[PDB]
Length: 57
Length: 54
Length: 109
Image 1: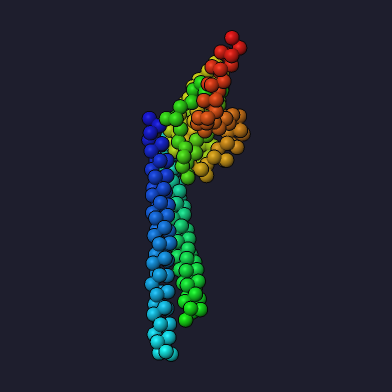
Image 2: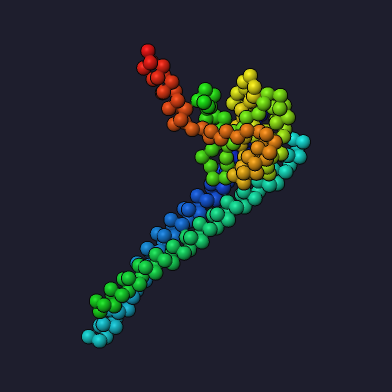
């Protein structure tokens, strides 16, 4: 039956879709990570500027 | 004929999986670019506003 | 019209690396085409041919294959006098033909 060849086509495409989808999930996770790491660094900058401002005060 | 066609495609179909893995590695390269772009845009915009406040 | 014969189960579509082609062959030449069509390009699986129907002159089959094969396949099909008709399950068009067939035959009466 044609299912012999058709399942080999579909197997390669399903494997392909899984690899691409896993990378797309990582891309979304990295975008969220950028917000989280930016939020940490701006607060660390504020805390340093605060310590300097208190010393000048 | 048929057995040689099956052996030939069983070899060649691996290049489709390889190019899909390269497409996944390009999506991960876009992940690394967009991480640095988003972090840069956020940090520099707010760092300047924080500096102007103090 | 393909609306007489086409159904989704005969097709491989909706995919990044996969395609369906459709080709017509004369009924005497079909006995050669059954093997010769798999030679027209690389990246074609064995038994990729699903027949849709025969008629008094010819057969039409779907061919299932990877995206790299298709332009070599279609050009070598034309070279070997095989006739391309890539109706890739156009559900909107088969429904439109069915609607106008029922409508026009009723409205004329």
